[PDB]
Image 1 (cartoon, rainbow, N blue to C red):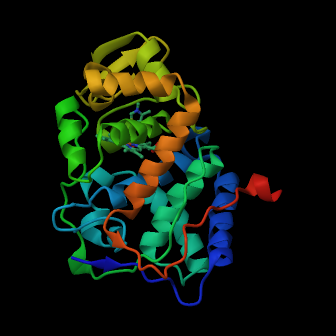
Image 2: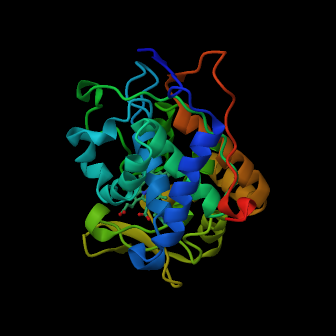
Amino acid sequence: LVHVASVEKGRSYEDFQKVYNAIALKLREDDEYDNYIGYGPVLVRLAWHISGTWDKHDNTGGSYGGTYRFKKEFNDPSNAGLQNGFKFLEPIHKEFPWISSGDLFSLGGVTAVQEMQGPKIPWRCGRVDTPEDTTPDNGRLPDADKDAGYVRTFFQRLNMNDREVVALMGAHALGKTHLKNSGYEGPGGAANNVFTNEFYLNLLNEDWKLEKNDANNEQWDSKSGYMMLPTDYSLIQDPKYLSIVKEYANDQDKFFKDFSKAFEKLLEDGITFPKDAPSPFIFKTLEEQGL
Ligand code: HEM
Ligand SMILES: Cc1sc[n+](C)c1C
């Protein structure tokens, strides 16, 4: 399967910076969502789940085709709750009907991270919508109730290595688990709509307790009111993972730098970019624009 990036006709940096600003302006406006967390965390989760279907072996799935717009992927049990990120972006797609679905879903994730004061993420245009029959089947996204060997093995399919996996998981400092979506409940920290390395700090400094929640699932709970998933707590159980966790709890700039590279890589897996294709765009935030 080859997927070649095709820039939307005649579009350039300024067009996409207008779509960025639209998403970012609405993130500021619709602030009440999920008890004032706002839409940013569900939008970086949406960009990860449309990319997370990729399989390196046959180049199926991935962010290129925008296939989450089809019922099979929209109704995947693993995507429960992401309909709220879709409905947030649907106004902006009506306003810029020229951007492809893959591009709009991935740029929403980029925009949310930078607007929640994360690192800049280089983003590239050119994903092309593909037919309903190209939609990957349910079951390619990871279970939460498993251990470190499972996480390592699952992420080899998206060929991410240990460092990349641990840097990507730091995004679980954002938002929260919702019992009616996943059977897990609670936030992982106090700053859950500002991008920081707090996931790593909480994992190493809190007093975790294995408890059972109302959906009868086990999760790690702390006195402070935070929770960690079994696959999250996995990172301090494995010796290779645990020493990268310590590296990111001791250096927030290295965390930001490595997250930026692994999230772009995540969003680009499966796409062939021609050598005459434009460079990756670095978008300015509303704040750097005085907007
Ligand atoms: C083995 C890996 C992973 C598993 C099992 C997993 C699982 C989960 C689960 C069960 C939730 C709760 C959903 C809900 O109830 O609403 C969640 C939320 C979230 N995850 Fe993951 N995740 C994984 C990796 C990642 C990665 C790599 C990213 C992003 C780079 C990510 C970003 C998020 C975000 C931002 C949320 C919060 C959503 C919200 O607030 O609504 N996840 N995760
Ligand atoms: C959202 C998610 S998923 C796992 N944790 C810890 C949070 C905060």
